[PDB]
Length: 34
Length: 38
Length: 38
Image (cartoon, rainbow over all chains, first blue to last red):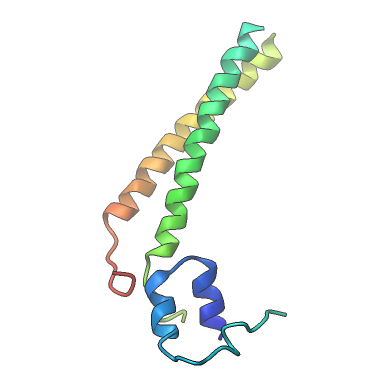
């Protein structure tokens, strides 16, 4: 949640892919900030 | 006029040096591990 | 004239301070381990 918002904000590549190992998880993938 | 013109080329070189610094400072954030701060 | 001339010496000191900063910022990249980003 909050890490993937952080890690994608700064281009950290390998952080995202292990966060995107949870396949069919679109709700936090398109989750919004405040 | 040439006093300001010499200052322009030094400032334009300065902001160009700040680009490569800022882009490289983007790169350390892109490649640095973190555990404790999570 | 001396107003711009005083500004030139402050700018020339500024870009000199930016050299040692940028060279040292090169040094942190030279010496920093990485595991997670690979």
